[PDB]
């Protein structure tokens, strides 16, 4: 019952190996071969060793010769085998694109069999294993995402020079007696009251011995003993189905904030002749999920019978598939810090630990296949992926089975997208459905992330109408254009494009001259945006920033304006979809922001950056998704309250005030006694009237306070008397041009205010530090302290990351105080005492000891 991951390999080009058989022979010389950890692509392995400069900086990645990766690279290792009494197996997936497998000078599998990133292989190498030093070598073939059923990067970033070839998941060495236990899982069904579940345990046993055996498969499901005995002929594999197990008052798994994230255990041993032969331990959550089409045709998810507005982002791994468990946990915790409930994985489906973490944290996941490459190459037309041949069909189906088998028992998984872009055809779709049936994968299947139907499953209930680049905030409030990306139906992937990271991240990823060009000529191409010509520059964004904003006076000016723009836009995108969720006709049922994060250092499609720093887009998403939230509608000037929490709330007061940039209050309304239902319900406080005397750019301060008088939401909008308007007839697939632009340039001349800061830190026994910062507006006038950003830094002024704040990017009127709380690992201080850098739009920059 041993399953031990190969900890590492030495790698080299097949340019250097003239006899393939020789690599896997014990004692093969590997002088000048590169030592690499588990889960490395070739180029990540070369990075580990020296060998090229940081691809996260400037055009470093362009200087890597890519031709060396158009030939196979070997992954070789020793294994010590102390005892050959047990059988020996290689159990793996994650080979990009395909591989020959060798043990002790014998080829045990070819690239025709071991083929496809997602396919699982379970190779009995018992005939080849001997006592003492054994050796295993994979000849890994080049990866082409347009030709191979694999992973590729589409238009998200720049192409990795090796195209991610290598082994990106673990290779398990498995040991067992005559019988191998495989594919153990629990079918779980919960009643609608959620107080009783029925559990069906299934497990495969395989007799790999020469002789017929009796095996007993026994252990525990959810604390309850179970046992079955079966007969197996030599080389026979059987699926064992256990009698039904009742579970009363199950500890139901819930999404974060809706309850706990309990997972039960399955523990099974297959025994032969009164001796253990193989063993497996797994987990499962008791949880119902549905995703059905509403009366408007929108895809509507529900978990444990509770309908849910999906609020998420498109999640991506590292560009070079470099795996780190803590980094994965850190990215999923940021999801919760943002107040998001879901991540989408378009392809690049993460290793198991990612889903374990997501299960433990209560983050929902939407895995599926990606667009624009081999997966959709048969239904794609003039895409980039190649039409399918007969040998493609088995590989795709086997990939589905393997993914359905890994994913089925993770309660965070809420669906599988079998298409993206284009829905599968009948033949390909039938293969997917058959594979999921064979895996007992019982979650919702979605045919596409666009509006395209599949033949068997049918309507998607989703839309992919863009945008992917600059649109003003009011755009998101559109329900008139059925071919655009307003707040209605299920928005599977959309953003307003460019997301300039913080200055600290910028100085790490781009040269002074690269950065100079970014503010001076946004029309120029940026390597750290995208390889596609459509998204190769920042023109649409830079044009809107100047127009709306005001022209940039320097780099600092451009970055500060970018943060306001991103905050404003991302906030509006989310707030519109929260508001329209409870519409009687065409509600918004989902929004996945494009994207949560980037594979590398980027200028677009991210909430948090590659270093986990947090910018205007991060804080705007966090503002929008707060659990008890007040917001202003860009279309109709209604002030709206959203309750994301699992309980109805009452006695709320919503207070809305307008101010000119000189600090003059121009409007006040106090709406007391508000009630709002649970799980995304809303209430309207007031509709702000057109107010006479407003400065061209003015402020709207929205404050929500509960029945105890506590402030639970503060939301401040910088608004213009000049409307943003759309030229709908100029719309393309990725944006809608503007016919007129708001004038927010008055912010340029907002008088200086003052803050007002005190910080302290507590190093905890759990290895975390909490830094508390009290901020006050200490000015003697009427001016707010606007857009005040606090960052935990070290003694050298470098940000401590990852970090989680309760709130940030706050605005304080004179005399007003707020207390903010940041949490992070003590060790990420790297021995420095903590400080807090506080910068505001009109309050300057200071740092205070913490």
Image (cartoon, helix red, strand yellow):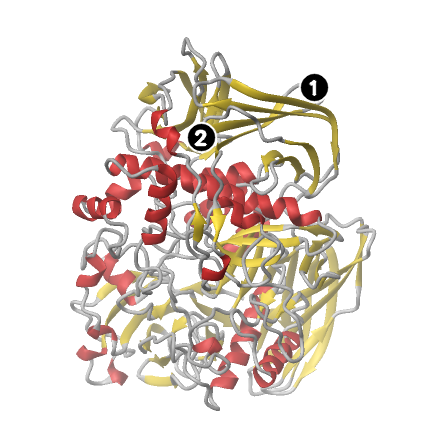
Q: Nearer the viewer, mark 1 or mark 2?
A: 2
Q: Dividing the image into 4 quarters, which one contains the N terminus?
A: bottom right
Q: What residue is rendered at 47% in x and 23% in y?
A: 660
Count residues near mark 1 (Cα–Cα under 10 Å), then give few for <14, some for 14-19, many for 20+: few
Q: How many marks?
A: 2
Q: Up-down: is 524 above or below 346?
A: above
Q: Dividing the image into 4 quarters, which one contains the C terminus?
A: top left
What is the number of the mark on residue 497? none
Q: What residue is rendered at 36% in x and 49% in y?
A: 541
How far across and how far down the image is residue 197, in percent?
A: 79, 57
Whether residue 114 can be seen here: yes
Q: Up-down: is 231 above or below 768?
A: below
Query: On the image, which quarter does residue 272 sit in?
Result: bottom right
Cα gap from disc 1 to disc 2, whole angstroms: 37 Å
Q: Up-down: is 602 above or below 656?
A: below
Query: On the image, which quarter does residue 229 sit in?
Result: bottom right
Residue indicated by mark 2: 696
Q: Nearer the viewer, residue 233 or 539?
A: 539
Q: Secondary structure at mark 1?
A: loop
View extreme (front): residue: 692
Pointer 1 and pointer 2: residues touching (CB < 8 Å)? no
How far across and how far down the image is residue 622, in percent?
A: 51, 39
Count residues near mark 2 (Cα–Cα under 10 Å), then give few for <14, some for 14-19, many for 20+: some
Q: Nearer the viewer, residue 430 or 452?
A: 452
> Going by the image, does 657 lie left or right of 151?
right
View extreme (top): residue: 780
Q: Secondary structure at mark 2?
A: loop
Question: In terms of sequence position, does the residue under pointer 1 or pointer 2 come before the other?
Answer: 2
Residue indicated by mark 1: 708
Q: Nearer the viewer, residue 267 or 67?
A: 67
How far across and how far down the image is residue 506, in percent?
A: 28, 43
């Amino acid at each position: 019952g041993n399953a031990t991951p190969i900890p590492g390999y030495v790698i080299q080009s097949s340019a250097q190996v003239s006899d393939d058989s020789a690599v896997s022979k014990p004692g093969f010389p590997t002088s000048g071969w590169y030592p690499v950890s588990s889960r490395s692509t070739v180029y990540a392995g070369l990075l580990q060793n020296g060998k090229y400069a940081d691809p996260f900086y400037s055009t470093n990645m362009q200087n890597v010769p890519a031709a060396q990766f158009s030939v196979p690279w070997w992954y070789r290792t020793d294994l010590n085998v102390d005892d050959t009494s047990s059988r020996t197996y290689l159990d793996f997936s994650g080979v990009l694109s395909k591989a020959d497998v060798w043990v002790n000078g014998t080829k045990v599998a070819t690239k025709d069999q071991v083929n496809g990133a997602y396919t699982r292989h379970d190779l009995d190498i018992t005939a080849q294993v001997h006592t003492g030093v054994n050796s295993v070598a994979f000849k890994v073939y080049p990866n082409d995402p347009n030709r191979d059923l694999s992973m590729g990067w589409i238009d998200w970033a720049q192409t990795p020079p090796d195209q991610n070839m290598g082994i990106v998941r673990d290779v398990l060495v498995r040991r067992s007696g005559a019988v191998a236990l495989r594919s153990a899982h629990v079918i779980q069904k919960l009643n609608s009251a959620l107080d009783h579940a029925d559990l069906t345990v299934k497990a495969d046993v395989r007799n790999d011995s020469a002789n017929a055996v009796q095996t007993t498969v026994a252990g525990t499901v959810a604390g309850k003993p179970i046992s079955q005995t079966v007969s197996l002929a030599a080389k026979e594999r059987k699926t064992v189905t256990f009698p039904l197990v009742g579970l009363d008052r199950p500890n139901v798994w819930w999404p974060a904030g809706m309850g706990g994230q309990h997972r039960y255990d399955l523990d099974l041993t297959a025994s032969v002749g009164g001796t253990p032969s193989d063993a497996a331990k797994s987990k499962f959550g008791v949880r119902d999920v549905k995703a059905t089409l509403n009366s408007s045709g929108g895809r509507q998810y529900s978990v444990n019978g509770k309908p849910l507005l999906i609020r998420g982002g498109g999640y991506t791994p590292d560009l070079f598939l470099r795996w780190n468990e803590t980094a994965a946990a850190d990215k999923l915790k940021y999801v919760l810090n943002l107040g998001l409930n879901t991540v989408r994985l378009e392809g690049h489906i993460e290793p198991d630990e990612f889903f374990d973490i997501a299960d433990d944290l209560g983050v929902l996941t939407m895995p599926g296949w990606e667009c624009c490459d081999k997966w959709e190459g048969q239904v794609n037309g003039e895409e980039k992926g190649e039409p399918w041949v007969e040998s493609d069909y088995p590989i795709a189906k086997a990939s589905m089975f393997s993914e359905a088998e890994r994913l089925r028992d993770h309660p965070s998984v809420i669906s599988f997208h079998i298409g993206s872009e284009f829905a599968p055809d009948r033949r390909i779709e039938q293969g997917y459905l058959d594979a999921m049936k064979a895996a007992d994968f019982l979650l919702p299947v979605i045919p596409a992330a666009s509006a395209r139907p599949s033949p068997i499953t049918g309507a998607s209930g989703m839309k992919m109408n863009g945008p992917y680049d600059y649109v003003p905030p009011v755009y998101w409030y559109d329900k008139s254009q059925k071919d655009r990306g307003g707040a209605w139906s299920f928005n599977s992937e959309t953003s307003a494009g460019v997301d300039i990271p913080t200055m600290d991240t910028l100085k790490r990823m781009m040269s002074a001259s690269e950065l100079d060009t970014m503010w001076k000529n946004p029309s120029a191409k940026q390597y750290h945006r995208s390889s596609s010509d459509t998204f190769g520059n920042l023109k649409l964004f830079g044009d809107a920033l100047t127009k709306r904003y005001g022209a940039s006076a320097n780099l600092n000016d451009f970055v500060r304006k970018a943060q306001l723009s991103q905050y404003e836009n991302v906030r509006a995108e989310f707030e519109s979809h929260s508001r329209n969720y409870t519409d009687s006709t065409n509600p918004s049922t989902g929004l996945i922001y494009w994207m949560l994060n980037s594979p590398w250092t980027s200028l677009h499609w991210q909430l948090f950056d590659a270093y986990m720093d947090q910018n205007g887009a991060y804080y705007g998403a966090k503002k929008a998704n707060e659990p008890l939230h007040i917001q202003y509608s860009h279309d109709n000037r209604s002030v709206v309250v959203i309750n994301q929490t699992s309980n109805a709330v009452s006695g709320l007061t919503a207070t809305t005030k307008l101010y000119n940039l000189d600090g003059t209050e121009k409007y006040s309304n106090t709406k007391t006694g508000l009630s709002v239902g649970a799980l995304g319900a809303k209430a309207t406080a007031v509709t702000v009237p057109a107010v006479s005397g407003l400065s061209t750019t003015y402020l709207a301060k929205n404050v929500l306070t509960d029945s105890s008088g506590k402030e639970v939401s503060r939301n401040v909008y910088w608004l213009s008397t000049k409307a943003d308007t759309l030229n709908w007839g100029g719309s393309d697939w990725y944006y809608t041009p503007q016919s007129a632009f708001a004038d927010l340039s008055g912010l340029n001349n907002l008088g200086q205010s003052a803050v007002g800061a005190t910080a302290n830190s507590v190093a905890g026994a759990d290895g975390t530090t909490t830094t508390t910062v009290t901020l006050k507006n200490t000015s003697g006038g009427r001016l707010p302290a606007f857009y005040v950003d606090s960052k935990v830094v070290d003694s050298a002024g470098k940000p401590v990351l990852p970090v989680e704040w309760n709130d940030n990017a706050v605005s304080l009127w004179p005399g007003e105080t707020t207390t903010l709380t940041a949490k992070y690992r003590t060790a990420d201080l790297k021995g420095s005492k903590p400080s807090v850098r506080i910068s505001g739009w009109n309050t300057g920059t200071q740092t205070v000891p913490a």
